[PDB]
Image: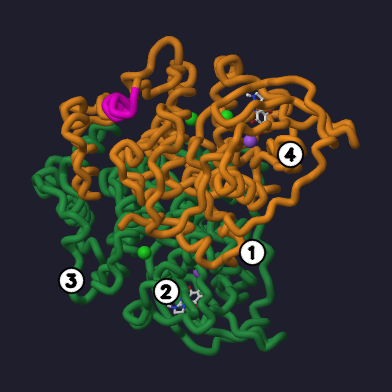
Chain colours: A orange, B green
Amino acid sequence: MSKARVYADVNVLRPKEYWDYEALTVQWGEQDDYEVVRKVGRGKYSEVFEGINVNNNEKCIIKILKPVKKKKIKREIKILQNLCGGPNIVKLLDIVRDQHSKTPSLIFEYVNNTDFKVLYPTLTDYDIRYYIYELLKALDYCHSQGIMHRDVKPHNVMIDHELRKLRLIDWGLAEFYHPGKEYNVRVASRYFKGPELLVDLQDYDYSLDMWSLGCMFAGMIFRKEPFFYGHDNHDQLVKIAKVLGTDGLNVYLNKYRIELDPQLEALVGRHSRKPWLKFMNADNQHLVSPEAIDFLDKLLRYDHQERLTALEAMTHPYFQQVRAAE
Amino acid sequence: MSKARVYADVNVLRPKEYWDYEALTVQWGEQDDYEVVRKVGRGKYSEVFEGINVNNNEKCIIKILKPVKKKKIKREIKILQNLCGGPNIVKLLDIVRDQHSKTPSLIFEYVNNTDFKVLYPTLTDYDIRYYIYELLKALDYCHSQGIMHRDVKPHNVMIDHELRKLRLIDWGLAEFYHPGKEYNVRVASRYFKGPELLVDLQDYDYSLDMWSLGCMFAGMIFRKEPFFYGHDNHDQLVKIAKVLGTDGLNVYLNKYRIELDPQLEALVGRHSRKPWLKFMNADNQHLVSPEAIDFLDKLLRYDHQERLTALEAMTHPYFQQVRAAE
Ligand SMILES: CN1CCn2c1nc1c(Br)c(Br)c(Br)c(Br)c12
Ligand SMILES: CN1CCn2c1nc1c(Br)c(Br)c(Br)c(Br)c12
Ligand SMILES: [Cl-]
Ligand SMILES: [Cl-]
Ligand SMILES: [Cl-]
Ligand SMILES: [Cl-]
Ligand code: NA
Ligand code: NA
């Protein structure tokens, strides 16, 4: 019966109203206070626009949601409210909806972002230490607040590179951690999904976000994005297996008494570990340091219980200059 | 050319006067302000007394030093002055000497200590987490201040168990860390000496104190003190080898291009690792937890560069309740 190694009793000790998001009653704001200026994204669950707050002429981000069940949207709203003001967490400013159709919109603070596909090739060795340190502040914060993000990936990390400012966004897949609870494993996006999700281990915890972080981080230092590129969920486990090796996978499956579907087992096969250094090449040589490698190594562990916690990660010597700069 | 992974440039960036202890001029205090009340210890370098400050009737500790070279005592005095007021560091209150013979005495804040041989059998599982957390505060502090203690052991950790207060004492073997400097390896006390000292690796750093901490910690959780019990310095390496295994030793000697004296090599022999769990027994079963073991495991590494830093150690999930209690 797997449990988190840290922050396990956070929601135990909070008032029930903190985590009982189904008992929330949304305080709808005024749809007219916010005007759409330009569309900047679309997704299965929404369309996203740059907008303005008419009252104060401030930019904002407006997420127009496609039809969504009451229970699902209250969970997202409650978690945003719970974390609002925390280190590098996106700020939810307002919640509104169209009177005729009841379509709800979520209103957030604006971030002058640069898509990671354009931004990450320009980051220096020091820059990556700095921004990952900023993203860990957000993860240590939401875990300490009893919440798992469950969709860490570059697409959900907004960065203003001029201001060197970062925000962790899109809390739609997030959940409250409760010891022993069995969660849906269809969360995160495929390339960032932890082995627990791929082998149907349902009683996972905050440590899933550290796997996802490690996937993102490996992509950045090796300039290979996504680092683990599977075509479907079976294939995702196979690509991991081919890097970490199947010896470590077998140990893991045995520890948690998991049995792989016969089909998956056949696809996974048998593989030796590929040492991190073998991913180094002329395209990433300026970023692959022994300290970067040691930190990555401690994130990308099959066993979720073995991974660095966010708190531990922040103290790794890889970030020592970021801390000194303070 | 081994270097510290953290705090390597602390003395580089400080004014020279911080670390140039030879340039200190002692400001002798008044020998008469302090009266010896009772002797509480003796050692190769001094005799120690409980005393009183006559002016304010406060207890103090008075260390009467045996004859000592000027350079050696200035180093101890400067380091005490540099660290005074830091988390759980003993406070040096005054420095005085006898007019007729020039014998110097060091005057410290008093601690109502209980010798570890009497105190540690009464510590609970939680108590050990708590006091080791307090000792790590001191080590992270002095390392951050550019200083290695080089004699961590229970005898130099004063604890008032009633007040739950800890102080790290006896800075006589301590030194300033300077990148690339070659230090004397005759420091620490035998049972707490790191493999670097035992194989004559001279360019060691703060990480030596983490080996010593791990020795102390293993003694506490397993109730086997000292944990590594060698009769002489060769035998000390052999007892370690017989626990950590010689495979890890060979890797280590090869990494730092060290060659063992032929005699030592013969005594060391060839040995498999003895897993931590094999030290568990009915005498320590109430203290040996998987988290305690994971933390120990990460301290007691041949390679000084692999060991947890004090900063990292403080964030380990083993201490999570101590942190929550705050
Ligand atoms: C896909 N695009 C690009 C910029 N940007 C996008 N989606 C965003 C969301 Br959702 C939020 Br919330 C914020 Br804040 C920003 Br900025 C966003
Ligand atoms: C051996 N004994 C027992 C108590 N105690 C001993 N040596 C001490 C030193 Br040196 C200091 Br400095 C302090 Br503070 C205390 Br308390 C000391
Ligand atoms: Cl979407
Ligand atoms: Cl580095
Ligand atoms: Cl002594
Ligand atoms: Cl525990
Ligand atoms: Na968002
Ligand atoms: Na002392």
Identified at 51% across, 77% down, the residue is: B164
Task: Using the image, name the chain to which the residue with label 3 belongs.
Answer: B
Say which residue label 4 marks.
A97
Quadrant location of the C terminus of chain A in the rendered image = top right
Magenta range is A232-240
**In-front residue for pair A108/B312:** A108
Say which residue label 1 marks.
B85
Q: Does the magenta segment cover residue B257?
A: no
* Residue extending furthest toward the top: A282
Q: Could you tell me the amino acid type at mark 1?
A: Gly
Q: Does the magenta segment cover residue A233?
A: yes
Q: Secondary structure at mark 1?
A: loop
The answer to whether marks 1 and 2 mark residues whose Cβ atoms lie closer than 8 Å is: no
Magenta region, main secondary structure: helix
The answer to whether marks 1 and 3 mark residues whose Cβ atoms lie closer than 8 Å is: no
Q: Are marks 2 and 4 on the same chain?
A: no
Say which residue label 2 marks.
B127
Q: Could you tell me the amino acid type at mark 2?
A: Asp
Task: Using the image, name the chain to which the residue with label 4 belongs.
Answer: A
| Relative image position of residue B128 (x, y in whole percent) | 39, 70
Distance (Cα) linking label 2 and label 4: 55 Å
